[PDB]
Image (tube, coloured by chain):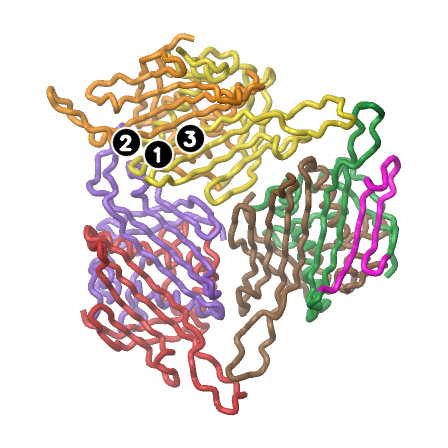
Chain colours: A orange, B yellow, C purple, D red, E brown, F green
Amino acid sequence: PAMTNIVLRDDQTSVATKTLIPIVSDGNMSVWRENAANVPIDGQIKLTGQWERMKDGTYRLNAKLEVPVMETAGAGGAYVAPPKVAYKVTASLTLYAPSRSTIADRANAMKMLSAVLCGADATAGTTLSPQSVTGDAWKNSALPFVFGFINQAFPT
Amino acid sequence: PAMTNIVLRDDQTSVATKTLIPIVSDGNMSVWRENAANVPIDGQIKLTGQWERMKDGTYRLNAKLEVPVMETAGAGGAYVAPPKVAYKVTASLTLYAPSRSTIADRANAMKMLSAVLCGADATAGTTLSPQSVTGDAWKNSALPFVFGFINQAFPT
Amino acid sequence: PAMTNIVLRDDQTSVATKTLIPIVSDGNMSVWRENAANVPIDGQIKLTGQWERMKDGTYRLNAKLEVPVMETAGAGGAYVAPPKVAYKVTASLTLYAPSRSTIADRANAMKMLSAVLCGADATAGTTLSPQSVTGDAWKNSALPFVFGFINQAFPT
Amino acid sequence: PAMTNIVLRDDQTSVATKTLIPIVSDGNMSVWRENAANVPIDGQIKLTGQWERMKDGTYRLNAKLEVPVMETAGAGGAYVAPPKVAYKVTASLTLYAPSRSTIADRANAMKMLSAVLCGADATAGTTLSPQSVTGDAWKNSALPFVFGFINQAFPT
Amino acid sequence: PAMTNIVLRDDQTSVATKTLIPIVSDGNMSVWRENAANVPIDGQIKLTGQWERMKDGTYRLNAKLEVPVMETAGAGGAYVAPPKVAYKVTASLTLYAPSRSTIADRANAMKMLSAVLCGADATAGTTLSPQSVTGDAWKNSALPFVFGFINQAFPT
Amino acid sequence: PAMTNIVLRDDQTSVATKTLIPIVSDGNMSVWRENAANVPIDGQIKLTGQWERMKDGTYRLNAKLEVPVMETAGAGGAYVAPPKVAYKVTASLTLYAPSRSTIADRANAMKMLSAVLCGADATAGTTLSPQSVTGDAWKNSALPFVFGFINQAFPT
């Protein structure tokens, strides 16, 4: 498939739209990046999709979303520098699919873990829109793994 | 929070429901497991949520879904072949969040990467339900990252 | 007993309510933490209750309340970092109860030291509400040990 | 401030009053002690308030309540057994306050931890009087941390 | 699942109730303890549930109930004797389940041995309630295995 | 007493009856065995009651129930395979009673651990009949220790 734009929606009070433009098509990876002004290149949101064949025939597929955070949002100026990038929150989905693995196996695994990350709970058929327009819908959610990852408390 | 059951839905032609019963709560990790008949303990669908504080104050949160495939018995051994597992398709979401990170930032990152894993594309607000009742909806999908993970060919 | 929420009241001008949610149930300890947005995880108020058996049979019971302080309260932003956590004020109650110690002994010790920390003075039956709704009631109090710990002057 | 008497109340069925007379004022510490008849000096209820400036500018303030239990005499030694002490239940509140810490912060911490030691629970503003005249009120209490300290089983 | 209290009934003439409160939850071990008045910690009734994976894949599950009998006071020596534990009556159920075992096998084994320990005899359907309010029902019972364990005389 | 038959009931959907006939009575050992059609001797359900006096006077009483699962035929190799036993699920109750123990101690311990293995929970008087005609009653039961032994997941 060809590289396309990737439009995401974050979880602020007012859901803001973020556009990742394709940058580069490499041999084992491909990269999408945000393009926002008065933001250092290091501060743009980055999406790296890479893949490799382990020595045992097993295929490792990594999708890495880096979200940078500047320290104090700055009034952009003609020759004024942006806030130095304070840190990065990183989230990587790794999929290990062995030699004998099949399309059905991979699809099942991906769909079920996606439901988990969208916080399926004891009640069957439960999920939360990752493209939800509801502001603060994820941080306020009490679903086991959404709440778990966000507020850093897994169920025990 | 307390551990609850977790009900997921696979991507077979007729969508099947899988239920993960809570098994154990360790000091740092918690484990849910399916309870299917005629399956060994090591062959059930397993979900492991673990977390550790790195030496730099950065916190690493892992959610690991193991989907096993058990072997099939060929009646040739002069005894019914013992029921063992063939292999495991594994999918682990890892979130690295430093000490300066907040609830707002962790939520932004989780929601955007969930949208990515649900095949967010150039068209804004595009997502595919991971609890979808549409059979084979994921394996047939052409959404960039759903397709790339299912078929081991990311956009390039 | 099961872990429950723990609701405390501080000593500002307007008494503010702080909720500690249970995080983890470990083998020798249990942890409660505040969950407040635009605050680094390191800056949340923490409560760690641990217990161990010394080699001589004596039981050591520690309850540790960590109160972090950020350096300059910051206007939360979409991709704006919180104030880096400036320092921690820590307060630990340690109870040493030997092998021959009894329920009555431990209850007596705990109640009397609690009265001391609530600042019982020469006048009998004297105490100060630790859940007091009166703003600034503790910092302004002149009770020997409340005043002592707060303003860092013990009676001599 | 000047050292005053300190009147506390235990948790017997009929609540008894204990009075701590000031004994000595050292350079860094001060000591109150009970004066009960037929008790050696080392068997009286003792209260020690000491403080030291750590090498990092952080100040450590300790308040230590020792409650002794004297042995009982069995008339078998061919002489009345000498009155000695059996053991000591000790409870020490320690406050670590750094150089950047203020009166507001020390007060917040002390009040909240006092509320904790008085069995603050999920219900807001919950506390048990440490000068309470209700006999056996503490040992019978089911408040989380009162119960946990008295019975050596914290919530888990 | 989560640890709950465990309420048992003994075989005294007037059947008494014992309550085991959870103390700690480890990864491979969970402990319940009784909290009775005027009994040391070591003299309380203890319940230990543990599990381990042997090197051959076979899981070993152990449930260990310790009923202590404390030393009766005795008359004074030099000083009054300290309270100490005389001995412990211990009862451990161990279940060995190899890799190829199923829920059916384990449930069948557990139910049948439970009926055995509840004194199944030649007449079908025979059983004795372990929660029975009938005082001295077990020590008086003549069912082969109950009587055998109690009176240390096995059917021969 | 004299050895009698022992009639047990399993946990199949339709509850089946198993009869253990006495085989042999030794001095410190007695054996019961099932006699089912089309099952080898080693595949029959076995029950072993033994006792021994340790070197410290403490008596050790063991009751061991072996439930074998025989190998399923499988297709022909060179010749038709001979019937053989696949594995054994084993459940052993061991009771340690020191010299100073009495009938009261042993009966109390046995009844309380029997109520435990029959799934006593927080609610008093809780029990599950081990001779119950309710099919699949044990494997479906959620009582902490019954469920724990069955599903190899202990309350934690």
Compute the Cα span from label 1 to label 2. Answer: 9 Å
In this view, the residue in front, D41 or D137, is D41
Q: Residue furthest left?
A: A79
Crowding near pointer 1: few (<14 within 10 Å), some, many (20+)?
Answer: many
Compute the Cα span from label 3 to label 2. Answer: 17 Å
Quarter of the picture holding the N terminus of chain D: bottom left
Task: Confirm whether residue E135 shows in the render.
Answer: no
Chain at tag 1:
B
Q: Does A55 sit left or right of A3 as displayed?
A: right
Q: Does A88 sit left or right of E9 as displayed?
A: left
Chain at tag 2:
A
Q: Position of residue B8 (x, y in %)?
A: 54, 27
Crowding near pointer 2: few (<14 within 10 Å), some, many (20+)?
Answer: many
Q: Does B26 sit left or right of D31 as displayed?
A: right
Residues shaded magenta:
F26-54
Indicate which disc residue A73 carries.
none
Residue of label 2: A87
Residue C28 sits inside the magenta stretch: no
Indicate which disc residue B94 carries.
3
Task: Confirm whether residue F43 shows in the render.
Answer: yes
Q: Position of residue A107 (x, y in %)?
A: 53, 18
Residue under the point 64% across and 39% down: E57
Q: Secondary structure at mark 3?
A: strand
Q: Is residue D89 above or below residue B107?
A: below
Residue F45 sits inside the magenta stretch: yes
